[PDB]
Length: 74
RNA sequence: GUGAGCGGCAUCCAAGUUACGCAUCAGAUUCGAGACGCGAGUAUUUCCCGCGCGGG
Image (cartoon, rainbow, N blue to C red; front, side):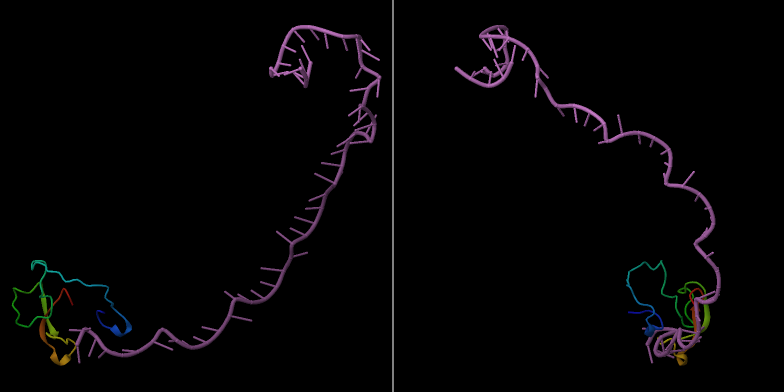
């Protein structure tokens, strides 16, 4: 029903959604927090080393790890 | 377990005081209730309008 934080006060209601099959050339799934030793070939753009979780929950500070985070997305 | 989860912009406050729509300006100049209804013309048929009868 809602996207993002502050859902309790009604922020980010979903009007609709769509899932579409697209060619890989359009964009990749790598625009996320990658492992430290992730292969360079699969990375899209510049990745800056930072501390982040690789699995949900990403807010758990005990699960944080040195990870590659895309600079063009943070 | 959507860097998620949880969280009052809320409380209080005078638009009010004072201020002349007023001073001046002809509804005036002309003209009749006094005039208007027939005592107007001969005798018996003539061209005609509707068709014995209505009628120039």
